[PDB]
Image (spheres, grey):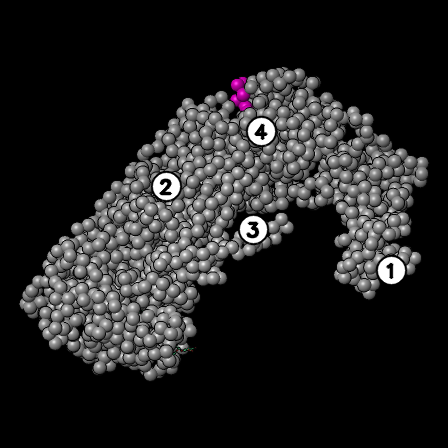
Amino acid sequence: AHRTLLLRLSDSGEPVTSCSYGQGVLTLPSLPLPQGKKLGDMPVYTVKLAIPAGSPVTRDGLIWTNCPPDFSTQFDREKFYKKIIKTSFHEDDHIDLDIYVPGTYCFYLSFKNDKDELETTRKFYFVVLPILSVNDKFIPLNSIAMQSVVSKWMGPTIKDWEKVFARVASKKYNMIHFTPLQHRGESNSPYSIYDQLEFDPTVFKSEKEVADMVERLRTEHNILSLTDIVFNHTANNSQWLLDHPEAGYNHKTSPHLISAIELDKKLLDFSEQMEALGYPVDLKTVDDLIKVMDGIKEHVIGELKLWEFYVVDVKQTVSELREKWGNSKSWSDDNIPSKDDSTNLAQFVRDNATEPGFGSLGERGSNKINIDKFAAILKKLHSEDYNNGIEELATKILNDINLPFYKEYDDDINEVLEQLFNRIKYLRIDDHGPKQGPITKKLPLSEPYFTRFKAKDGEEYALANNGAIWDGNPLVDFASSQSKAYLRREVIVWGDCVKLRYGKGPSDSPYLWERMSKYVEMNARIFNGFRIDNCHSTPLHVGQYFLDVARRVNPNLYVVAELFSGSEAMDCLFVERLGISSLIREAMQAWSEEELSRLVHRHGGRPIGSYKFVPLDDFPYPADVKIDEEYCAYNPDDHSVKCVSEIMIPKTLTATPPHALFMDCTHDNETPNQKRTVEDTLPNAALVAFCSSAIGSVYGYDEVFPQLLDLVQEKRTYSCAENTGISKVKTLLNNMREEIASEAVDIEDSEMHVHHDGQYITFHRTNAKNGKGWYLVARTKFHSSGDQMLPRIKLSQTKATFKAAFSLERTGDAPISDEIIEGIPTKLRELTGFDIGFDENTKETSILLPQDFPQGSIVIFETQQLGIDDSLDHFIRSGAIKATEKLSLESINYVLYRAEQEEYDYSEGRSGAYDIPDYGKPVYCGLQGWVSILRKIIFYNDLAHPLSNNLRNGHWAVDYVVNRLDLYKDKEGVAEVQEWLRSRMERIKQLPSYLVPSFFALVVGIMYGCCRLRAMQLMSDNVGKSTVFVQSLAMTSIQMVSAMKSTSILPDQNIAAMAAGLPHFSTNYMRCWGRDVFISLRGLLLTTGRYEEAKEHILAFAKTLKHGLIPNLLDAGRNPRYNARDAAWFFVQAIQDYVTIVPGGVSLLQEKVTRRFPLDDEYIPYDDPKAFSYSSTIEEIIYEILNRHAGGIKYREANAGPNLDRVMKDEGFNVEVNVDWETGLIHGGSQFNCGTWMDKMGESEKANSVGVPGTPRDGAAVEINGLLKSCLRFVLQLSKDGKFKYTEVTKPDGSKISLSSWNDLLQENFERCFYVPKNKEDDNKFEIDATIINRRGIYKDLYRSGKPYEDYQFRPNFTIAMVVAPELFTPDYAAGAIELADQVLRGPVGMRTLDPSDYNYRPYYNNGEDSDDFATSKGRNYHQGPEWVWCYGYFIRAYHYFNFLTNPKCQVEGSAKKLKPSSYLYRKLYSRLLKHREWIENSPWAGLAELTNKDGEVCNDSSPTQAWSTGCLLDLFYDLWISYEE
Amino acid sequence: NCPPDFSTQFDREKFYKKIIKTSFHEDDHIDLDIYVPGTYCFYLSFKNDKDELETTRKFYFVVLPIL
Ligand SMILES: OC[C@H]1O[C@H](O[C@H]2[C@H](O)[C@@H](O)[C@@H](O[C@H]3[C@H](O)[C@@H](O)[C@@H](O[C@H]4[C@H](O)[C@@H](O)[C@@H](O[C@H]5[C@H](O)[C@@H](O)[C@@H](O)O[C@@H]5CO)O[C@@H]4CO)O[C@@H]3CO)O[C@@H]2CO)[C@H](O)[C@@H](O)[C@@H]1O
Ligand SMILES: OC[C@H]1O[C@H](O[C@H]2[C@H](O)[C@@H](O)[C@@H](O)O[C@@H]2CO)[C@H](O)[C@@H](O)[C@@H]1O
Ligand SMILES: OC[C@H]1O[C@H](O[C@H]2[C@H](O)[C@@H](O)[C@@H](O)O[C@@H]2CO)[C@H](O)[C@@H](O)[C@@H]1O
């Protein structure tokens, strides 16, 4: 059905962690195949790789993976296959990886570097677990009960073994671990294997004899089998080692151990002549050690010639200096140090005159000097004649060269004998170790470090035997040349075994790899899995090759390994590459009760009430996605991985900690009788069995054997004594886990609470789906610590049921047999007296233990959380899609957003945002305010967060979500969304308090995802199919467009009105701004598809035309402020954008609006009948603006005086505009004016700036004339199509100019007036006074403004003209000017409003500055440095356009040979939007700020989300979409 | 020093990169589009047998004017 997982990748190709489960491995969940399907019928899993759009990896990117393309193809570690990444700047690419067989798989990415070179990422691994079934019943991996049995203690016959099989089958183990069933070596230790290719001749004879026994275990007792596999060593007496001695490290293969070989056999010879030479044989005196050690110093240490292995032979070098003194013909270099620096000269010879392998170990005299180059250094430093003091100089140099070697020798020798007299004590003197037998041939003073034998090639070899360094790094091969452990005697050896020298591959040991390969696949044909002892000491590439050979034979190979590497990270890497299925953990390692409770806490599960993952505001919501409309397209027989909700965003693949196999006692650790007591066997095994993982035990733990069995010596056989000790309890524990395994699946589905009080350990296992659970109280018996009483156990909102209780008591000592291993007689007494009190009011269960509860006892309770049934998850994960069926792009604003001021508008100031105690209020009142806070909480499972605390302290926030929508119930689809929230929040309140936070975030997250998907469906295709970043920008359109009560865009009704920004521009007269509305109209409404809403805003402002101008401050159409010369031209540009984009948009020109202001610019007759007087089509409204500007306008503002602007001066109210017809551009403004978007009016009385505008832009503004040129070009082509009827234009005198002549006037004079040429000679054509200048190659900011230096200022306003009127610019002039803005004026997120090199540059904005600074106080800085985000949009839109026309590297051929931008330009565009994508990701408000201080510094006064800040970035994506993505 | 397109002016000392597609079987062909008459030259940079950088002579060719 649906077995697909989504693995999202970062911009560098690394997998994204959806949750913080800790250091882990990308593991896929173990699930059975669909009903009646085998391996090959269909892919086991499909990993959907998600590559971000426009990421640097997409540039000629390829996905590599060693996954075979189909089931017929075998798996190869190093054969990777190609996959093409479909690059796009809008849409992410999804590439499927079909997996047909479990195993180890990795993937890496190759792409084109920014240096046009090839680059590769890391290899990223993911493991598909094997499928374990017995007959036809699936065995979940975390329900495995493993019984480890040793072969040589089960009887000499097969039926003697099948009696042991029946005993462990009665205890209901489902898996048996075998010590290797091969022919054992001399010492008969199970791990020193004589021959790997044939089994034990005592019991078996062929593969079919043992294969039938394992298959018999499967069919008879329903038990799977696995063995140990030994890679690191073999027995010291293998007949194939005589044929192939190179399989281990010898004097030929590993020459560095030659020094250690002679030390071993010199100590063994001293053991032969020990008291024969001296006196101490085997005494227990501290002096006896010292005297024998003094014999070692004089008979073996002092008998190897001072060890020339390090030191250069001094006199044998001088002897080899006179022999050929003359072939060496001096030197010519002058770098040789003089005899003054006696040490720098010593090492200078070491670097130039040395044979290969100097300093390292080899033969006896491996380190020697190149004679021919040494004498050449001597001759050029002293003399060419030898007798001239060369013997003294050459010896002085060589003696200094051996100074570090001699001190390297004293530090080595000290560790040789210090290690000796420390082990021989423990080896002989009873410190804690016995066997102080007089030094025998079998028990010499030195344990054999090397196995000596005469090979079939006649020669003699010395293969050593592996072991373990005390506290050394196991990742280092101590037999390799990098270690000096065999020399310094830092090795605890195993004489039973012998080295196995693998190299870099089969080329270094051909027969060893061929033999181990046939030995691995032999057991792979028979058994279900392997067990690897000391896997950390086996090299990676060695373990990788053979485990893949086994998986080719047995595709469902189950791998266990005792892995204790350097850290958890190294543990995960071994699990990643080797494909380890489970790690062995030992419960006997716990020294105390607190260490045991912490071990069980690690492998028990997740905390109770843990958060559940949900797709939130960090996912793409494609409008074309399949949906489970009622979470019903699932069948249990399909065994499909479930999506999170009704939306079919597949289950995410995230790193989870590697699976564990918790062993209460292995075959290497001491018995509970030894380390603790026998009574602890019951509570210890119960705590382990309760862990949510695989469990195991060694045979004898349940049968309470007295002491750990010696794997080497002991020959006694297991007892036939049935049902001894814990065998009855293990039957109960394994049978209980069989019931739980049927429904518990993923890591979020099993929760746990563990408590430790003195000698008691509490374990509470809980299933998160149904509420079923177990409660375990186990009193541990580490030692007889006396009587301790446990406090009252209290469970909230839970009912308890007594299951079983037992006590383990010792009845004396164990029998002493010599032919059978018998355990200690034990009584298993059932306990009673547990009082389970239940308060039918508080729904609280109390549990009181009985006083007869001795140490070594347990008691199990069946528990069930109240309010949770099996049908709870389905009710929460369904219905939300149907509930959002009637939502609109306006109504979603009330469900998701609404600022507190916006909410106060609907609630008259009564409601607002929920106040979280000890935290604050969410940013929005809707779900976005919750999701912005919950995303980090769910990621870290922060159950201690103030919101998490409040959610379980009461149901206030739960009811706050549902009661909010009463304000907006009458809106489209909000009532049905509220009812879904009401029904789901009501069911949640019936749950335990501690579970409310996890379920509250789940209900909110599901409805949020359904609301965000519904938005993408109602929007256009370019948005509804794009990256998270584009959709996040599109969601800002819903944040701004809302219906209000205190304001609107129409004076008669209350409809949807786009806010300027939240929360500072949302209520009353502060919401709508004509300049702000129509700059963001194309991005927030046209790019998104809000055509009808974009028409309403054009018509509403068309009603308030006056003086041929559109008002900036719109008071919903009653008494609007006409202090703007920018708005009228941004308004007429939005009309062009509407007609260009909207299909049939020409119909807007003939739409009649009710002109509610008289044509003769009258006063404010809002209530007069002359308001509704006359109508006006948009066609004549456009012409009314063009003709009124040309015919000249002259007026003082209506209602002039302080009642409007209480700081604007008297002369400031009389603004005005006219056109200089020698150039054709529009002037206007004064030094007391703010008619542009940089409208910051001073108000500081302490700084003497009241009424002085911070940025008056009087005269010709670049944006105004650029939009004027865009309007003229628009109406000219419109008249050509019969849609515009006007070409006449009146002048103040009476003259007429055709619209084309005015259009040509700008084309001939615009660039001439504004461009500042970089050529100092071309100043005579572009009208420039070079005295007041800053940088040339710049387009002006103003023409003939009040202060002439403000004309020649670098400001980002010229880019508005570059975007709307590109014909006014010669390409080479514009490209160089916009390149300066990129280097100088471009900030990280915002565009610098003023050149930093200017003297007026103050980039920090503080609207509360109470100082005497004439430029900074009370916010006069507003547009003199601070970085605005919307100007970045217009900047990059023209930066893309003019780099595409000028730079040849920004073009590439394509569809119909039409030039599309190269990946070099997309790369430059993508890099300039990373700070914008970071901003909207890590902001509580889901948008882009209005303003930013210098260099990304957050401005507190700036509105955190602005309409035109995000709308101008949506304009860029529409340019690249509407022009190339066809 | 051949300009990549007609928009780019000619500079004597501004040279542009071109990648040689190395093969042991197939020769590589690299086009030089010339839009305006003048003096143009080309030289080659490669990895020496000493793993160092080496450069050949500048080789010129003249595009005659159109009269
Ligand atoms: O209800 C009728 C209304 O009539 C009159 O309105 C006038 C205002 O009183 C008067 O101050 C002025 O408003 C201007 C403003 O002066 C001008 O600079 C510009 O807006 C700027 C602010 O200047 C600037 O400081 C900043 O203010 C933000 C602030 O940064 C933000 O952090 C947060 O605190 O919100 C503040 C705004 O509330 O930014 C804004 C936007 O860039 O334009 C304004 C409108 O023209 O002129 C008004 C003319 O009607 C009465 O005076 C007023 O009391 C009445 O309520
Ligand atoms: O004791 C007051 C109680 O209310 C607090 O804050 C919220 C409340 O939960 C909502 O119902 C809201 O409508 O009123 C307050 C905010 O205006 C705390 O949530 C709660 O813990 C506290 O005890
Ligand atoms: O009035 C302020 C002043 O700021 C800048 O002055 C520049 C000057 O023009 C340059 O020659 C520069 O080297 O020195 C000053 C900055 O350190 C503006 O260029 C100037 O127009 C403006 O008036």
Same chain shared by disc 2 and disc 1: yes
* Residue A1246 x/y as whole percent: 35, 83
Say whether disc 2 or disc 1 marks the residue closer to the N-terminus.
1
- Residue A224 covered by magenta stretch: yes
The region drawn magenta spans A218-225
- Is residue A114 visible to us here? yes
Kindly check if marks 3 and 4 are in contact, taking CB atoms under 8 A apart as contact. Answer: no
Q: Secondary structure at mark 1?
A: loop
Q: Which quadrant does the C terminus of chain A fall into?
A: top left
* x 46%, y 41%: residue: A63
Residue pointed to by mark 4? A549
Check disc 4 and give the amino acid type: Val
* x 49%, y 44%: residue: B28
Say whether disc 2 or disc 4 marks the residue closer to the N-terminus.
4
* Rendered position, B41 above or below A1324: above
Viewed as shown, does residue A716 lie left or right of A871?
right
* Residue A380 x/y as whole percent: 82, 59
Callout 3: few (<14), some (14-19), or many (20+) C-alpha neighbours within 10 Å?
few
* Residue B57 x/y as whole percent: 55, 55
Residue pointed to by mark 2? A649
Gap in Å between the C-alphas at discs 3 and 4? 45 Å
